[PDB]
Image 1 (tube, chains in turn red, green):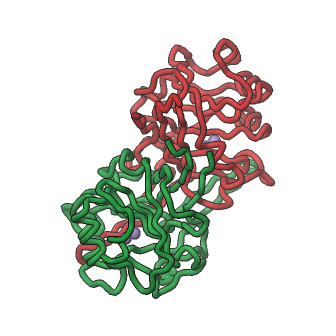
Image 2 (tube, helix red, strand yellow; image 1 turned 180 degrees about the vertical axis):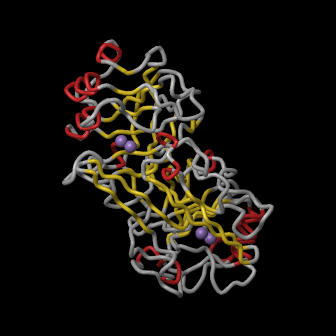
Image 3 (spheres, protein in one colour; image 1 turned 120 degrees about the vertical axis):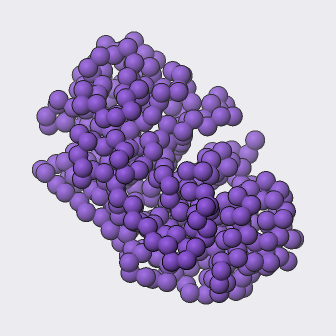
Length: 205
Length: 205
Ligand SMILES: [Mn+2]
Ligand SMILES: [Mn+2]
Ligand SMILES: [Mn+2]
Ligand SMILES: [Mn+2]
């Protein structure tokens, strides 16, 4: 029984989207004696997080409306580290991908220590498939699940079929295969996302 | 397989320590058409959270040094909702509490939906016993594990023997007995605590 921690470290200087200074977290501390107490400011879309429909809608469901039963369940890691530029319907047709599947995608982003602007992303063609195939949720090892797609069709195509999106996974030391996924978000209410601790278990039970 | 969410909701207006209005979380939201994006600010000791040795020491370990192997593991939920004022050595001698047990304390705090200044707490006599018995960790259904104790002897007795302190649990709907605990902290580096999503499973094997 090994736990693989596939969560991104949160710290000032961490890889953030487009390396934008304002997307960086701040931690303030105070030590009155031996008592050390901190406060953290962070974008909900920081490192390992779970997107909610409200991101890409407006009467969109929040983080809260997505049940823990959908996040603390079995999952399948798909190795797409052979993929260049973007994941296409081709790369996900040939994989074991059924209805109510939670698929985590290990791509060459798992191996970038700093932000890469040309990160492998889930194209609309790939997402529209995944939606009509009837997957439960998709995780990507990238802070955003899509780029170079204005009107955000990838995102919109998942959250339309209430498919939970997990961004910011660190899947370097993970082998393609089925695992017990623990995707535990901060119990934030009414928001477009929540930062998450995502663990894999080799439970094989 | 039933998950029990024993994590407090995080929202402006939530119960915080002594109702200090500065300990309240903040959130800023932005809406370019249908993209919605948020930023949270919160005390790392807000609601359900894991304490680190740093709080109550300085050479003491930060919230990245408590491994997930001792936070995502079998737990014992002990009923002490018959206890008044404070938990004592007598109150934790009678219970099936063993070395390397992770013990979550259900008390009258779970049935308090607002902060109460007279909260049940773990007293030094009890925290010392649990320290020399060799428990792996103790969870409390109060935002703080002690009060009316200057020098913080309960904290220190436990963070001294690398015993983990988990605070802010919501154990009203939780029957005394064994569970699988997922105490999944936000992966913030070099801090005195980190907010946690704590889940309880009934897998029993
Ligand atoms: Mn995002
Ligand atoms: Mn997104
Ligand atoms: Mn605390
Ligand atoms: Mn504390």
